[PDB]
Amino acid sequence: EMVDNLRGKSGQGYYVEMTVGSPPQTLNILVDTGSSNFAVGAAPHPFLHRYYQRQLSSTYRDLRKGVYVPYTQGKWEGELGTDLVSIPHGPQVTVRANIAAITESDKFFIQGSNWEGILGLAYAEIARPDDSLEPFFDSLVKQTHVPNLFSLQLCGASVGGSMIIGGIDHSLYTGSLWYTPIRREWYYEVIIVRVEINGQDLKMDCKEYNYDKSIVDSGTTNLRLPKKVFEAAVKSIKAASSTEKFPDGFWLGEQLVCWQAGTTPWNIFPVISLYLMGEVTQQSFRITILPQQYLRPVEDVATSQDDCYKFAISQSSTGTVMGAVIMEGFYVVFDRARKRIGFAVSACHVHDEFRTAAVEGPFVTLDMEDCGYN
Ligand SMILES: CCc1cn2c3c(cc(C(=O)N[C@@H](Cc4ccccc4)[C@H](O)CNCc4cccc(C(F)(F)F)c4)cc13)N(C)S(=O)(=O)CC2
């Protein structure tokens, strides 16, 4: 019943069906582990197929307080209230939850996207206007018997996946689940201890990988890297792929790269390995990212004599973001109860006949350094 409860469009997030209000109003809601506010369109907008109509809900309560949330991409403002909320293809429960009713927005809603709101699944510490605004998942756990854990299987124009609330579905992964500690409960903050491209260590002090934090963020498309790390990674991927020369704009995500249909030279692009801090001192495991993940297909019938891609690795001034292109093809367990994130190869894993995405360990390092930036 919870399997295949996510849909989406490539590059535009993954969403789950929800209802708000009494009687229930059905909305599609983007699943975002990178923020902590539940917010829904609540006024007409050119890109909204539908919106929350507070006047039609008998259970709506105005909190008489406005709220503004600026993401990396897009921003919105709205009015806080509470109302009853369900998830038709999740646990059969009804929870009263905080809801920001979006009345104004800028570059938030996406033309043709199919979602009308966002579900911030991270912790209260980053909720706006402040941490007293209890996030949705906290309310769900407090009000029901749902275990304090959820798991995401994001699959690679239309895409799909599963959000399993309150548990782990073993049919969605193979091999072992490897856990990395949640360093601080605000974002889902983790620690990267090593980065390799084409098996070659980037050779930086490991704190650079976590400047100034590293997070797991289903609401962000790309792998985003601190400038120093980004520049080193791009240099190494360029070197690996030097049999072909792409315009500088491709590497900056400003331009597509296109090949005749069916002829994408996957083999010239390297595998990227991200080593995550283990649960035991100086131990780690790695997740390996194939080019089928970090070259994001851009669907466009106009260009359809070709396969065209955007480089889905980009620069960040706010730390590492392991976004959707990293999560796709892994089964990712947000084990809040035990303050850890689990990774396993998912049933929808990425692979060709030569290489496959992997989650593998353990690895040991002799270096005693804490890789946390703070
Ligand atoms: C999913 C649309 C999309 C496409 N991109 C990008 C993008 C960043 C976001 C992003 O900011 N995602 C938000 C949620 C979201 C926003 C707009 C549309 C859909 C989803 C995440 O919440 C960001 N998580 C970290 C963060 C940053 C600032 C403030 C907050 C907080 F906590 F909400 F205040 C969280 C979405 C997106 N990048 C700039 S990018 O490098 O991945 C390339 C393109």
Image (tube, rainbow, N blue to C red):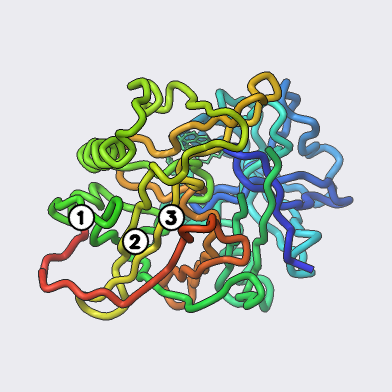
Disc with the residue nearer the chain's start (2 vs 1): 2
Residue at (41% x, 71% y) in the render: 340
Gap in Å between the C-alphas at discs 1 and 3?
Answer: 22 Å
On whether ligand 1 comes within 8 Å of the CB at mark 2, the answer is no
- Give me the disc on residue 225: none
Please give the residue where the numbered disc 1 appears in the rendered image: 201
Numbered disc 2: secondary structure: strand
- Give me the disc on residue 216: 3
The amino acid beneath tag 3 is Val
For the C terminus, give its image quadrant.
bottom left
Please give the residue where the numbered disc 2 appears in the rendered image: 190
Asked whether disc 3 touches disc 2, contact meaning CB atoms under 8 Å apart, the reply is: yes
- Whole-percent x and y of residue 185? 39, 62
Is 246 placed left or right of 199 in the picture? right
Q: Nearer the viewer, residue 285 or 340?
A: 285
The amino acid beneath tag 1 is Asp
Crowding at mark 2 (Cα within 10 Å: few <14, some 14-19, many 20+)? many
Quarter of the image where one finds residue 239: top left
Gap in Å between the C-alphas at discs 3 and 2?
Answer: 7 Å
Residue 208 seen: yes
Quarter of the image where one finds residue 315: top left
Residue at (77% x, 50% y) in the render: 20
- Whole-percent x and y of residue 157? 68, 37
Numbered disc 1: secondary structure: strand
Q: Nearer the viewer, residue 60 or 49?
A: 49
- Whole-percent x and y of residue 143? 66, 71
Residue at (70% x, 24% y) in the render: 301
Is residue 337 shown above or below 235?
A: below
